[PDB]
Amino acid sequence: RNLSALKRHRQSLKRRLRNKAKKSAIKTLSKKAIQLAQEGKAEEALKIMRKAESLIDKAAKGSTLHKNAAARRKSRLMRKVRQLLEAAGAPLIGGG
Amino acid sequence: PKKVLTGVVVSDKMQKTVTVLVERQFPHPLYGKVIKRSKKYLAHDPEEKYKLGDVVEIIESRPISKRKRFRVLRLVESGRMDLVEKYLIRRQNYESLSK
Amino acid sequence: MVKIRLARFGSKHNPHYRIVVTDARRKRDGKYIEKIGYYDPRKTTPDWLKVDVERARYWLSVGAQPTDTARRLLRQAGVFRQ
Amino acid sequence: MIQPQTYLEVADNTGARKIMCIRVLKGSNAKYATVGDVIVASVKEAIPRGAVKEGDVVKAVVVRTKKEIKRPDGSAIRFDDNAAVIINNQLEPRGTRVFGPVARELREKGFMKIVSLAPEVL
RNA sequence: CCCUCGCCAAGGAACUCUGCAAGUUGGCCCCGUAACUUCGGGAGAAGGGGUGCUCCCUGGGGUGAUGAGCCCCGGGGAGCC
RNA sequence: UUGGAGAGUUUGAUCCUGGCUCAGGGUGAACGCUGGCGGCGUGCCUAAGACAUGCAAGUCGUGCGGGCCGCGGGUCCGUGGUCAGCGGCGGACGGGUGAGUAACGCGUGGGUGACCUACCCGGAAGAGGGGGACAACCCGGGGAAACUCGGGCUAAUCCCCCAUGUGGACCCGCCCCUUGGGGUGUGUCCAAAGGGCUUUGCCCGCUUCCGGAUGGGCCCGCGUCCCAUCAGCUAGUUGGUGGGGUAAUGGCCCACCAAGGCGACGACGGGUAGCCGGUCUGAGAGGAUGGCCGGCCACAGGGGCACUGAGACACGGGCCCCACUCCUACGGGAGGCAGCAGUUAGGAAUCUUCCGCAAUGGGCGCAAGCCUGACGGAGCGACGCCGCUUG
RNA sequence: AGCGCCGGCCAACUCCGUGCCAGCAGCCGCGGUAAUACGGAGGGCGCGAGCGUUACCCGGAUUCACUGGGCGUAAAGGGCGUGUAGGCGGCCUGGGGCGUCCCAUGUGAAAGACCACGGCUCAACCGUGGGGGAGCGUGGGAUACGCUCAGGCUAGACGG
RNA sequence: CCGAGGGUAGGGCCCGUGACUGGGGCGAAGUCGUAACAAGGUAGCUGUACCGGAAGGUGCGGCUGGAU
Ligand SMILES: [Mg+2]
Ligand SMILES: [Mg+2]
Ligand SMILES: [Mg+2]
Ligand SMILES: [Mg+2]
Ligand SMILES: [Mg+2]
Ligand SMILES: [Mg+2]
Ligand SMILES: [Mg+2]
Ligand SMILES: [Mg+2]
Ligand SMILES: [Mg+2]
Ligand SMILES: [Mg+2]
Ligand SMILES: [Mg+2]
Ligand SMILES: [Mg+2]
Ligand SMILES: [Mg+2]
Ligand SMILES: [Mg+2]
Ligand SMILES: [Mg+2]
Ligand SMILES: [Mg+2]
Ligand SMILES: [Mg+2]
Ligand SMILES: [Mg+2]
Ligand SMILES: [Mg+2]
Ligand SMILES: [Mg+2]
Ligand SMILES: [Mg+2]
Ligand SMILES: [Mg+2]
Ligand SMILES: [Mg+2]
Ligand SMILES: [Mg+2]
Ligand SMILES: [Mg+2]
Ligand SMILES: [Mg+2]
Ligand SMILES: [Mg+2]
Ligand SMILES: [Mg+2]
Ligand SMILES: [Mg+2]
Ligand SMILES: [Mg+2]
Ligand SMILES: [Mg+2]
Ligand SMILES: [Mg+2]
Ligand SMILES: [Mg+2]
Ligand SMILES: [Mg+2]
Ligand SMILES: [Mg+2]
Ligand SMILES: [Mg+2]
Ligand SMILES: [Mg+2]
Ligand SMILES: [Mg+2]
Ligand SMILES: [Mg+2]
Ligand SMILES: [Mg+2]
Ligand SMILES: [Mg+2]
Ligand SMILES: [Mg+2]
Ligand SMILES: [Mg+2]
Ligand SMILES: [Mg+2]
Ligand SMILES: [Mg+2]
Ligand SMILES: [Mg+2]
Ligand SMILES: [Mg+2]
Ligand SMILES: [Mg+2]
Ligand SMILES: [Mg+2]
Ligand SMILES: [Mg+2]
Ligand SMILES: [Mg+2]
Ligand SMILES: [Mg+2]
Ligand SMILES: [Mg+2]
Ligand SMILES: [Mg+2]
Ligand SMILES: [Mg+2]
Ligand SMILES: [Mg+2]
Ligand SMILES: [Mg+2]
Ligand SMILES: [Mg+2]
Ligand SMILES: [Mg+2]
Ligand SMILES: [Mg+2]
Ligand SMILES: [Mg+2]
Ligand SMILES: [Mg+2]
Ligand SMILES: [Mg+2]
Ligand SMILES: [Mg+2]
Ligand SMILES: [Mg+2]
Ligand SMILES: [Mg+2]
Ligand SMILES: [Mg+2]
Ligand SMILES: [Mg+2]
Ligand SMILES: [Mg+2]
Ligand SMILES: [Mg+2]
Ligand SMILES: [Mg+2]
Ligand SMILES: [Mg+2]
Ligand SMILES: [Mg+2]
Ligand SMILES: [Mg+2]
Ligand SMILES: [Mg+2]
Ligand SMILES: [Mg+2]
Ligand SMILES: [Mg+2]
Ligand SMILES: [Mg+2]
Ligand SMILES: [Mg+2]
Ligand SMILES: [Mg+2]
Ligand SMILES: [Mg+2]
Ligand SMILES: [Mg+2]
Ligand SMILES: [Mg+2]
Ligand SMILES: [Mg+2]
Ligand SMILES: [Mg+2]
Ligand SMILES: [Mg+2]
Ligand SMILES: [Mg+2]
Ligand SMILES: [Mg+2]
Ligand SMILES: [Mg+2]
Ligand SMILES: [Mg+2]
Ligand SMILES: [Mg+2]
Ligand SMILES: [Mg+2]
Ligand SMILES: [Mg+2]
Ligand SMILES: [Mg+2]
Ligand SMILES: [Mg+2]
Ligand SMILES: [Mg+2]
Ligand SMILES: [Mg+2]
Ligand SMILES: [Mg+2]
Ligand SMILES: [Mg+2]
Ligand SMILES: [Mg+2]
Ligand SMILES: [Mg+2]
Ligand SMILES: [Mg+2]
Ligand SMILES: [Mg+2]
Ligand SMILES: [Mg+2]
Ligand SMILES: [Mg+2]
Ligand SMILES: [Mg+2]
Ligand SMILES: [Mg+2]
Ligand SMILES: [Mg+2]
Ligand SMILES: [Mg+2]
Ligand SMILES: [Mg+2]
Ligand SMILES: [Mg+2]
Ligand SMILES: [Mg+2]
Ligand SMILES: [Mg+2]
Ligand SMILES: [Mg+2]
Ligand SMILES: [Mg+2]
Ligand SMILES: [Mg+2]
Ligand SMILES: [Mg+2]
Ligand SMILES: [Mg+2]
Ligand SMILES: [Mg+2]
Ligand SMILES: [Mg+2]
């Protein structure tokens, strides 16, 4: 009736927490910056947008994000913010 | 290579897409005779430059939509509405094969 | 890893291996990447060993990993001689 | 308060879905059946190829009722449907599972087998 | 006690010659709708969803003048009890 | 040119047409009568019915901290075994089966400027400084079991934080290219874990990048059965725009817009079937077939789902619903042999609850080595072929 | 040492018993008192740890006919026109080279099959080497015929 | 939101079965006649129509695959 598969389920539950928690944050921040960039509010958008990008690549270190996801999330994050600031300018920090 | 095919446009009624009909011959695998078979491909035309009646070449491409896996390669001939007739008349006969 | 090893052919109480390069995840007697020699353990013929040496050196360069009892039959044909 | 004509749900896996009471087996002229009482019924609706089929005249013990039953401790319990379990002449279920809760009253009346098979007893 | 009327536990036609009587159903908008047919129909078949108020965006018409006001027919979004 | 036989039977008789029938080869066979030996094969074709019991996946103390026992000897240290636990790596392979599927599933040839790839190899550089959790253990409550609740503490190759930037990622501009390919400039962002010995030197690990190799995803041309007494089918339908999602393209998912898409070259519908290498027959052409072996696919009681992960939507992992069975102390719990054997049902019918890791192979490990119903062999059966005997 | 068979197809013949019975049977057919055809027997034929039956596949079946059939009377011409799609199409010249044909090259896994050899005392089984292929991709070529485009013609067709 | 499935209601296709009923095949040891084969004793066959216990008959039109 036994196994260390039990062990392996025990672990997955814990990795699941760390993952979800990490991904939650990325969306919270990305959207936060995108929100700011709409009403931009350019310095702040850019400020939060950096905090996102950092957290994304941080996730791509592990099992959370495959590298190409991180790339992709970053690509779409940036595009949105920039093109949003085009409806008023101008970029107060970096970047870029 | 990317497969390349030549055929007549029979529809322009989609936006940014043409229906290109490609025809082919081959001997009957048992009865020998050379036989024709045809097939419609939805070909990508981002430029809405291809008209009904054009004879064109299409090249297999990365998938554009469900069902569209070809972009239009180039014009070859224009104004082959006689081909388009052959197709259109055939569909119109179908109203007469029912019950 | 991709591996160099011994696929058993022949028959019962009558082994006949094909020293072969295959993915480790294959089954023993399964589709192999490339054949590179054979080996009769019962030694019942003059050349109970044959090894393309020119080939086995390639795979090693490119990262193949021979089994223990294949490493040897690569020693015996001096694929390793420096 | 089950009486002839009352339809009951059947809470087992005999294949019967619905039964119509035709008699309450409690003496010569009992008007109503409650929890723990046996009725005779007609099978009005059943699923294909079960132990029992539409038309069969079966016995059943009532196991939950929409009229509340009262208890000597001053409480009462009430279920959302009237349901019964089909039995044989030795008060044993003819099915092998029973679905839904049943009334504890069943135990004191010797429907021990049904009481255990039940997911809950209230 | 009778008339006219309101409610009713569990049951639900077991009432009775007979569901007699009384319930149920119930307008409008939308979805959807069988046998059979003289091709009209059967059809409101059946069955089902919607229905108040508040705010915001928006389409067409009448009267004006082409506009405002007034009146008519809507559509989409977010909510409140 | 290595290859091609026909016969009986319609008549009083004949010729012809024409059907029936036979001799031949084949098989996962079965049945009868009979039955000595050996070798290689080979054996649930039916209920993808239901299954008692063992066994089929684990390993590393050279990641970590502990208990329990013992060995060593002055409470402690060491050393060893064992037992969990935290941490890796395996568990996605290998084994089963053929239910579903008429489909890009498979076969064959191609495309990816639209893509991934653990361990393996080649090459570029690098490991500075902090902090934290949770188990194990102690302490409480709850059971017949399955078992778990909460309080507290502690280690690390666990987690996090900053530093560092060969590199790498992303937006904008520019150059080459030409679907998202290669390079560059500014901006921003991302690394790490140490263990061990013979100890200023090794070994195994750790980190980011490039390329190889290998295994994959997706896409396209052509091929793939019966019924037209199935002739019309289609609203995510066909295309578009934007976005969501993924490793990646795509109506794969959504919002909006347009009115399209398919079909006698057979859509739609019904039926049947996993496909191939092959196999069997046949002069050939063809017909029939897909058992064993190899390739791919699909499935894991019937369904749905995602988590973990390089990789699964995971046969012996998880969640939920259903059907069925069992356990109980009657409160409550458990299971999934289409892995190897074995039982039962069904059937004309189909095996030993064997032996071993010695060999080949696979997993973990520096290694010794541990596990392996893969496999190597043995057992039963005239099931097949081959050999041999009763002189 | 067994098993099938001994009318014809088909290799293997006599005696008894039975008497349209009991029975055989793949087809044609046997049995009604002299049965090589039933049952037994002697004998014979065929194979032999096998023989025979049932089932199914291909063959014989040119009996779905591509190879390789047919339609007055054997089964088979639509009751007759008109005509859509399709299939097919006269003479001459050029252009293109789609069919077609040739060369090169990639692919066409392993096993199996085929030829050689070799290992188990043979074989079966098994190993080593050899031979190729259709079919698809790529490159180059040919242009008779079919195709396509272009220009001529008059014997088909149509008109005066 | 979507969602296994569950529930309600109405449809389509297919299999099994059913009082009874329609013919069909066969058997054969019957009843009734004798329609076809000969000019088959009314030449036959035919599409259709009406009719008869039954083969069949008759009408209309057609065919010769009709004897003399
Ligand atoms: Mg473990
Ligand atoms: Mg939030
Ligand atoms: Mg990662
Ligand atoms: Mg992941
Ligand atoms: Mg698109
Ligand atoms: Mg009934
Ligand atoms: Mg009441
Ligand atoms: Mg009530
Ligand atoms: Mg009622
Ligand atoms: Mg009711
Ligand atoms: Mg009554
Ligand atoms: Mg009464
Ligand atoms: Mg009435
Ligand atoms: Mg009334
Ligand atoms: Mg009313
Ligand atoms: Mg009303
Ligand atoms: Mg009323
Ligand atoms: Mg109806
Ligand atoms: Mg009516
Ligand atoms: Mg009508
Ligand atoms: Mg209504
Ligand atoms: Mg309503
Ligand atoms: Mg509302
Ligand atoms: Mg009002
Ligand atoms: Mg109000
Ligand atoms: Mg007015
Ligand atoms: Mg106005
Ligand atoms: Mg005869
Ligand atoms: Mg005759
Ligand atoms: Mg005769
Ligand atoms: Mg004949
Ligand atoms: Mg036998
Ligand atoms: Mg025997
Ligand atoms: Mg099976
Ligand atoms: Mg069954
Ligand atoms: Mg069972
Ligand atoms: Mg074991
Ligand atoms: Mg280590
Ligand atoms: Mg040990
Ligand atoms: Mg341990
Ligand atoms: Mg597998
Ligand atoms: Mg096997
Ligand atoms: Mg299958
Ligand atoms: Mg189908
Ligand atoms: Mg296809
Ligand atoms: Mg393909
Ligand atoms: Mg891994
Ligand atoms: Mg610490
Ligand atoms: Mg950093
Ligand atoms: Mg939409
Ligand atoms: Mg898009
Ligand atoms: Mg993935
Ligand atoms: Mg879709
Ligand atoms: Mg087609
Ligand atoms: Mg057809
Ligand atoms: Mg089916
Ligand atoms: Mg199947
Ligand atoms: Mg032949
Ligand atoms: Mg098959
Ligand atoms: Mg088979
Ligand atoms: Mg296989
Ligand atoms: Mg499934
Ligand atoms: Mg499942
Ligand atoms: Mg099962
Ligand atoms: Mg399941
Ligand atoms: Mg698993
Ligand atoms: Mg699972
Ligand atoms: Mg799966
Ligand atoms: Mg597996
Ligand atoms: Mg299992
Ligand atoms: Mg207890
Ligand atoms: Mg529980
Ligand atoms: Mg078990
Ligand atoms: Mg049996
Ligand atoms: Mg068995
Ligand atoms: Mg075996
Ligand atoms: Mg081993
Ligand atoms: Mg080993
Ligand atoms: Mg190792
Ligand atoms: Mg074992
Ligand atoms: Mg014989
Ligand atoms: Mg013979
Ligand atoms: Mg003879
Ligand atoms: Mg007698
Ligand atoms: Mg005699
Ligand atoms: Mg005879
Ligand atoms: Mg005789
Ligand atoms: Mg012959
Ligand atoms: Mg033939
Ligand atoms: Mg035949
Ligand atoms: Mg022919
Ligand atoms: Mg003929
Ligand atoms: Mg005739
Ligand atoms: Mg004619
Ligand atoms: Mg006609
Ligand atoms: Mg024509
Ligand atoms: Mg032509
Ligand atoms: Mg010509
Ligand atoms: Mg020409
Ligand atoms: Mg050409
Ligand atoms: Mg070739
Ligand atoms: Mg080959
Ligand atoms: Mg020899
Ligand atoms: Mg060979
Ligand atoms: Mg050949
Ligand atoms: Mg020419
Ligand atoms: Mg011309
Ligand atoms: Mg002329
Ligand atoms: Mg639903
Ligand atoms: Mg549903
Ligand atoms: Mg449910
Ligand atoms: Mg009848
Ligand atoms: Mg009858
Ligand atoms: Mg007459
Ligand atoms: Mg007469
Ligand atoms: Mg006459
Ligand atoms: Mg007449
Ligand atoms: Mg009469
Ligand atoms: Mg008359
Ligand atoms: Mg005439």
Image (spheres, coloured by chain):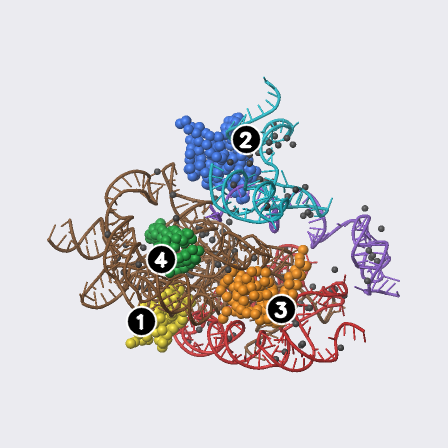
Chain colours: A green, B orange, C yellow, D blue, E cyan, F brown, G red, H purple
**Residue sitting at 34 percent across and 69 percent down?**
C63
- Res. D5 image quadrant: top right
Amino acid tagged 4: Ile
Crowding at mark 1 (Cα within 10 Å: few <14, some 14-19, many 20+): some
Asked if badge 4 and badge 2 are on a common chain, one would say no
Q: Position of residue F299 (x, y in %)?
A: 46, 55
Indicate which label's residue lies in the foreground, 1 or 4.
4
Asked if badge 4 and badge 3 are on a common chain, one would say no
Indicate which label's residue lies in the foreground, 4 or 3.
4
Amino acid tagged 1: Arg
On residue B79, which mark appears? 3
* 3D distance between C-alphas at marks 1 and 2: 91 Å
* 3D distance between C-alphas at marks 4 and 3: 58 Å
Q: Callout 1: residue from which chain? A: C
Question: H58 or F251, which is in the foreground?
Answer: F251
Above or below for F177 versus D81? below
On residue A93, which mark appears? 4
* 3D distance between C-alphas at marks 1 and 4: 65 Å
Task: Name the element at disc 3.
Answer: loop
The response on whether ligand 78 sits within 8 Å of label 1 is no
**Residue sitting at 60 percent across and 65 percent down?**
B52
Task: Name the element at disc 2.
Answer: loop
